[PDB]
Every structure is written in structure tokens, then in C-alpha cells.
Image (cartoon, rainbow, N blue to C red):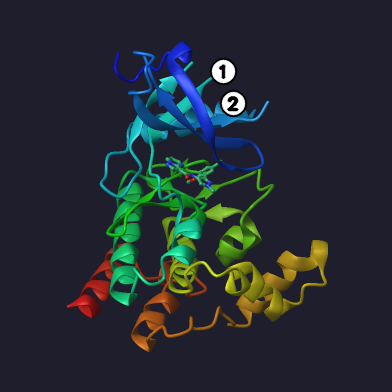
Amino acid sequence: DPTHFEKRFLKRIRDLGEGHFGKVELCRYDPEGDNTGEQVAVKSLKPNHIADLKKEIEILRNLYHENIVKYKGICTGIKLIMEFLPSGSLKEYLPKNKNKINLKQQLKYAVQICKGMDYLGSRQYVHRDLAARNVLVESEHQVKIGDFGLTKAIETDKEYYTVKDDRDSPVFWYAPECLMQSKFYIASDVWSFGVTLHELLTYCDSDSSPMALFLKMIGPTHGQMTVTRLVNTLKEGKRLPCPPNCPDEVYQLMRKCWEFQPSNRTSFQNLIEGFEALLK
Ligand SMILES: COc1ccc(Cl)cc1-c1nn(C)cc1NC(=O)c1cnn2cccnc12
């Protein structure tokens, strides 16, 4: 079985990244024992979260798209084995490559994120975690959606999935329905995409991050009152400002991701056409 990675041959090299419950490591699968084996990215949990990882593995095993990270297999306790992309995420790549990545490349990356996301939605799934940290860089010409840790299936003939465990949520990327009722629609991922586009256009600058910008708008002195204050700001019609050097035509497309009601938001296909017209 080419998708079965034996524990004895999966050699840990170094850490790539870490979250609250999981971590990704660079390993080499070396059955020959001479360091000629293929490098792979391995996701595992820190010592039920085990059940969630098993559902995440089965989602990725069945996704096939040029802008979705490639599933390679499993190591059985279970580890998810995937292709290794040495450039890492946009969050680490963009601050180090501003000279190479111009506006034309930023908009092509935006089209690619939209294509991967439209494919996920056609498979009846809602991501719930679309942010620059979850987009990997294949090359200066290609990006891939690189994590599916919070992904849920939407029931047939239903418009949304309700999440009970909303602990450690990326609130500054969440649409009003997610914050107010814990409801996740395909239109909620469109809202998240608008915030990821803002990150891409600022080259993931820490000082102008969505969290930093919203906290200036609401006040960084609230604590447990932060989310209510965020909801009030959005209900008032306030939104993230236009990124520096971002043309108005691009900002207007970003604004279409942030219509208050999910049913009024632009689709991923409408965004692709919008960006393709600006690229011509
Ligand atoms: C999407 O990334 C993550 C997802 C979950 C976690 Cl827990 C950490 C990262 C992460 N943090 N950082 C800083 C870098 C990461 N990842 C890579 O560099 C990487 C390279 N190839 N690859 C393939 C699949 C997944 N990740 C990678």
C-alpha cells in the first residue's frame, strides 16, 4: 500500500509549525536508510481531538485539486502524511519576498485561493479557518490551501452547519452569523476570504494584521467583552480599511465579501471573474 507509512522508516527532521492541539513536522520517509528518501510534512496531535484528526484525514484523502495540498498517506494513534512545501505559509513567505511578489502576482494568488475554495464548497464542505497562515506556497507562481483542521460537511439541502465547540476561534476572520449564532455557511468562507485578501495585500505585515486593525477600531481594553464590541462595529457598517497601494477596483471586490447578510455576498466564481478582468 503506497499510502501506508511504516513508523520505523519515518524519520523526524525538525518542526515546521505548532498550534494549541496539533503540530506539523518535516520528516524523511527513508526505507533504504541512506537519507535518499522523500521529504514529507507530518501532522500529529500533542500528547476528543483524536476523533477530529481522523475526520480531517478522511476529508483530505478525498480532495483532489491543484490548489489543495496533496494527501500522501497515514502512519498508524494516527499521523497525517502530506507533500512538503519548503516555502511554508504566506504568513512567513510574503514578508521576505515583497520584491518578487507584485500586484499582478498577488491577484493571481487570490484567483488560486478562490479556485481551491470553490472546489471545497462544490464538495459540500465549509472550511471555517481561511487565513494566510493556512495558505502554503508551492512556488512564486502557485499557492495551495494547506490545512482542514476545522472543516465540516454541510447537510444536503441545508445552508449551514452549527458548531458547539467554538473555543479558540479565529474571531477577527469570522462573519457576523459565525460570531452571533455559531452558524457556518459557504458565504462565511467568502467573508474569511476577504480578510485573507487584506492580509495578502499587506504582505502579512504584523502591525496591520486584521487583529491589530480591529483592536484599534474597538479598543484593546475589553477582554471578555472583545467579541460583543466586534459585533457592534460590524453591525454599524464599519469594515477593515483599504490596504496601502491597493487600487479601489480591488478594494470594492473585497467589500463584496463583507455584506452583512450571508445571502447578499459575492460568490467565489464572481470574485475569480472580477480578478481575471483586472488581470487582462
Ligand atoms: C498550514 O501549515 C500548518 C498547519 C498546521 C500546523 Cl499545526 C502548522 C502549520 C505550519 N505552521 N508553520 C509556521 C508552517 C507550517 N506548515 C508548513 O511549513 C508546511 C510545509 N508543507 N506542509 C504541508 C502540509 C502542512 N503544512 C506544511
Q: Position of residue 140 (x, y in %)?
A: 31, 59
Kind of element beneath mark 1: loop
**In screen coordinates, is 223 left or right of 130?**
right
Instruction: Indicate left or right for 279 with 36 as reference.
Output: left
The crowd level at tag 2 (other Cα within 10 Å; few <14, some 14-19, many 20+) is some
**Extreme left residue here?**
280
The residue carrying mark 2 is: 50
Residue corresponding to mark 1? 77
Give the image quarter of residue 70: top left
Q: Is residue 139 above or below residue 172?
A: above
User: Is 119 on the left or on the right of 187, as rendered?
Assistant: left
- Let me know if residue 131 appears in the view: no
Residue 279: which numbered mark, if any? none
Check if mark 1's residue and mark 2's residue have beta carbons within 8 Å: yes
Element assignment for label 2: helix
Which residue is found at the position 81% from the left and 64% from the top? 223
Residue 117 seen in the figure: yes
Quarter of the image that includes the C terminus: bottom left
Q: Position of residue 189 (x, y in %)?
A: 45, 58
